[PDB]
Image (cartoon, coloured by chain):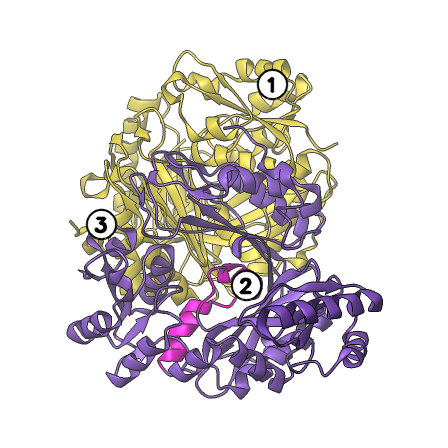
Chain colours: A purple, B yellow
Amino acid sequence: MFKKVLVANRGEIACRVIRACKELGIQTVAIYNEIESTARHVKMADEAYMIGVNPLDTYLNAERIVDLALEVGAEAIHPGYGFLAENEHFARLCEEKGITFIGPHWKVIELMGDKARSKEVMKRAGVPTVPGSDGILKDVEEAKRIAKEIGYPVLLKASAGGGGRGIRICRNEEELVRNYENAYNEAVKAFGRGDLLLEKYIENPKHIEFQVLGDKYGNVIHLGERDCSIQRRNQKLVEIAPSLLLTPEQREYYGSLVVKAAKEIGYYSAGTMEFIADEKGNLYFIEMNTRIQVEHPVTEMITGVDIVKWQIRIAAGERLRYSQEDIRFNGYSIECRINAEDPKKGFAPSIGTIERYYVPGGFGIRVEHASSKGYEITPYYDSLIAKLIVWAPLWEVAVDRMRSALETYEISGVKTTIPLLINIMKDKDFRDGKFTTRYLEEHPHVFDYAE
Amino acid sequence: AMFKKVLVANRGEIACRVIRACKELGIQTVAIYNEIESTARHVKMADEAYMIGVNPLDTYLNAERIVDLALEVGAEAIHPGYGFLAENEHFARLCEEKGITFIGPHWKVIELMGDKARSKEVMKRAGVPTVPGSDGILKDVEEAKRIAKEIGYPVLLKASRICRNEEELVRNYENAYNEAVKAFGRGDLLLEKYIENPKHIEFQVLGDKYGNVIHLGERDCSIQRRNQKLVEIAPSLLLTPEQREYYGSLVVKAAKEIGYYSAGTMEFIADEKGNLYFIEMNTRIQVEHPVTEMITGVDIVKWQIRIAAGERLRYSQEDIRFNGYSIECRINAEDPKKGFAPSIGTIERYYVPGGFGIRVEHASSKGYEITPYYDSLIAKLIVWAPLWEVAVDRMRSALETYEISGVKTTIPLLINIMKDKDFRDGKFTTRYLEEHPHVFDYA
């Protein structure tokens, strides 16, 4: 077990890691920028060092961080999420200097950081991806055949022109033909080459993600899935575990598949496979995060597994003491991001100073936060004030508990997402499990609230 | 028949606890407060709040004004919390007479189990062991002589000081009859077997209004001073599963014999071997109920509310399992270096810890003012883990990050208790604080 760990992060995730280390009996080192000399994670660590020439260089200067670790005798670095956590060169430099990086091997971080090289890994493991042409379409006949084979609707896009002159949705064969001609000709005009690619169109999808955890001896489990469809611009606002979409059979089927894929690339530590999903529970792989997920607590609440503490144990060489048979899914857990942003104005950040600040607690309530009165939201760092997490045996009780917790979470000095989140908990569609990404676009009333 | 509106006749953390249970149930809430508490958390959390009372205690102790307010605002029920009027039979009778549902046991049960001698006889008929000693007031010193011979040394004299042999017997008896005449007007003394190195062990009961009564295991609240609990655990490390079900069965049997419903606690002293002797019953929610919630999954307060509205308790004893260990620490505004004297002042810096296995019961923010009129409790910090040792580490690590300035608190003492070897090994009695003075050594 490590004697000292350095947390190359800030805010709530630094406090989460620091708490896991203290529980393990591990000494901790924090890093900070001078504009946050009073930061909570600084007070919580056994040792703290101001480094960096500006607020971001503190957390992004790989060489400065590995060097500080060597100076102060830290055997391992936890990177949290964001900043350098999925930076293969930071992980490689840790290994080269004899410091253990708490995460997957640097070669896996590099592998899964590339979109298409990630898609192929998952295809080769048997993890479903979005179907479509296996490159350029030979002709219109083949487009008709393939569209028939993967199911309408589908997308046609020109192959040339770097990005894309514009994608066309085709709902039936007739539309496929018209759109094939129009796109072929517009692409001859624009780039000189009419060749088209085809893709299955997943309309109005949900965001569903699976959690994996592996030790450095090939033992790898899944911790079921989360639904994080309630998001704007790919920023998640509400995350639930498990999904309401999937049955136990689907859950173990896809879970088995991501375990299979993780084993084939030699994954260890924590990781997440994010998918889009249709109404029927068909999932398609989009991307993998090779780090702790922000919303990992909801998975912790329903499985009993302490993911961060197991990252640290795994990095130190311990075996994962679980078989998949041990992993059970009990009740439901909801997490809401309490952000300093204004949902009535496009979620514009609300920089300022927290004045009133009362944290909720109770049966089934957990708070991940690093704020008190006087906490300053600067433009340098993300807008997150707190993650409010609840657990209950029944979905509806979980919703009521999250509503009642939010209604008691008092924050003044900045605008927050709390009133919007309360409206979501009170919304009939949300209570009935009916939401996709796009939930917010399709429910504008949740933006109606007092000042 | 679920209530539409409930009035919470209490303040502070327990009021917030009840209000949260009510909000989750979809019940409108009414708070009461004194003018010195215009900004109190429970006022802010409730849907409705009323300033009443001619002084800070009158707010919560004037039964008639509170019942009349409930009728005025259309509250169907009153939750009394703990302390104040919670175990006041007259308050409960007054609710029943005016058509208000009191969230608790029937007022006749509150009257019964508030009486030491009636409580003892309840337990004698149920088969629940009591402390051996005199069978009422001692007739004289001669009768005390017989009773001491029969029950075994050591023994105690107490009015309605340890006595190990006959000399000490008379010597302490003349002086003690006289010293109790001085103070209470009545010299009547009782004698009791002296239990050396005792633990405090409490059993939780929960009953519905249809005769169904369950127990929710036990708690060890031995870490205490002058009977003020500081650390509470569930379950005990003392009892085995068989002892737990044996004593649990007995307290269920007693409760059924008195027709108990709602939540209640049977407090016992226990000797080295796990023998229990009944001391008293609280006919109300316990302060340290959360540790029991953490290990059983049962929401005790919300079940009080459901039971009072006429629901059946949806559990048999076979469903009640005890999973892991839960520790609660009372974080009080008091100074353990000066005999735990209250530390009045205003909270300045205030960071609540959170995380996996952490729960906080509190009603404070920056600016919360600790007055002399009310108890000193700032927060209850509760943790759970699958294993005792991890629970201790989790509480130690939660306490070390719980930052409170502006007043003195029990936090440094609690941290030292969490890192003390004896405590970690389960080795503690009600004398723990006397026997470990080093825990008072801190800056």
Q: Which chain does the residue under circle 3 lie in?
A: A
- Find the distance from the CA under tag 2 to the CA under tag 3: 34 Å
Residue for badge 1: B70
Amino acid type, mark 1: Ala
| Image position of A220 with respect to A420: above or below | below
**Label 1 neighbour load within 10 Å: few <14, some 14-19, many 20+:** many
How much space separates mark 1 and mark 3, taking CA atoms? 52 Å
Q: Chain of mark 2?
A: A
Image quarter (top left, top right, bottom left or bottom right) of the N terminus of chain A: bottom left
Closer mark to the observer between disc 2 and disc 1: 2
Q: Quadrant of residue B419?
A: bottom left
Which label number is shown at residue B94? none
Where residue B118 sits: x, y (%)? 56, 34
Residue A65, image x, y percentages: 23, 70
Where is residue A26? Give x, y as percent.
29, 70
Circles 2 and 1: CB atoms closer than 8 Å: no
Q: Can residue A82 be seen at all in this image of the molecule?
A: yes
The region drawn magenta spans A292-316
Q: Is residue A306 magenta?
A: yes
* Tag shown at residue A35: 3
Element class at badge 3: helix
